[PDB]
Amino acid sequence: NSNNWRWFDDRSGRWCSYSASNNSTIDSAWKSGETSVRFTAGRRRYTVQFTTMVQVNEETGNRRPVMLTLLRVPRLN
Amino acid sequence: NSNNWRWFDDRSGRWCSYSASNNSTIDSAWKSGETSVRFTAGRRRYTVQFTTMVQVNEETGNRRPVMLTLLRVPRL
Amino acid sequence: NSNNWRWFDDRSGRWCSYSASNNSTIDSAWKSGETSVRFTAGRRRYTVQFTTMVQVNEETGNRRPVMLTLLRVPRLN
Amino acid sequence: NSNNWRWFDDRSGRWCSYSASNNSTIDSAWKSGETSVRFTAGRRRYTVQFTTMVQVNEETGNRRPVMLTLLRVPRL
Image (tube, rainbow over all chains, first blue to last red; front, side):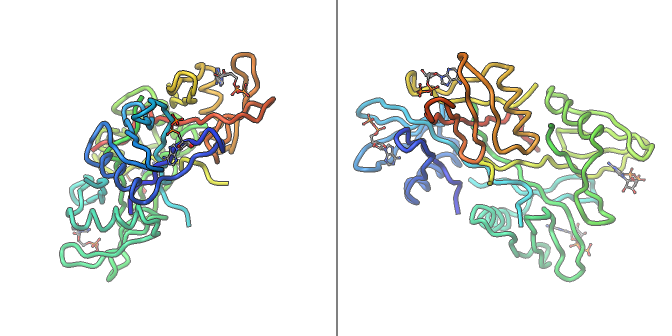
């Protein structure tokens, strides 16, 4: 029970979701008012920066966009 | 932290916050994709229905409106 | 093509929508950064206050709650 | 005013705003419940798909991500 963050994969041309651990790490940081947060995926080190909504590969500087899904209000049946 | 859920008090004409415990129970059900959530306040039994955004007194059927305020949105 | 505002009717226990004119008046005010806006419905004069999200009957002071619907991102098929 | 729509530029690694005209065309289609919207920028033809949140080059099939930033949310 946390928000679903996504990162854009320019290869498949699609928004992909994070692992449940990486999604929880990111969403905890977001909830606490952090401007950035670190995690690893594929044995690669990432910072997500909330101020620019991008994910940075710390080793190469390569920036991929992230998004926060918005759940409908009201909710649908 | 968590999202801020309120119910409207027609007596006082204002939007009131739930108890931190009730808030987290509701927001957890909201995040998990549930269509409703059940809890107790003033030693009374309530269901919040997310598809009508109301709080139901389980004794009376009495319906009070609820709202979601987002703690934080993406900016620039 | 504007946001859908609703007011709560304690009588029917339901969120109701405004007329297209009253919805457009309210949403224009919202979009421009106004804190309040005036309209009439049922030959009765209302102010909506965005700071408290309520609708006030100017003659009686009676307050009913309003809400702004949030459209899902992404949109569903 | 209107909502702020952006597309991601992989060349510069940043989120860019559309032209005010393109923005209003997109946000109007968004408000009306459309599932897509069509326009032109850099004298090129694009469709934005709201169900995948991407901008499609109509010549190439090339997909760029788009985002919605809300100008204003309810608070207290």
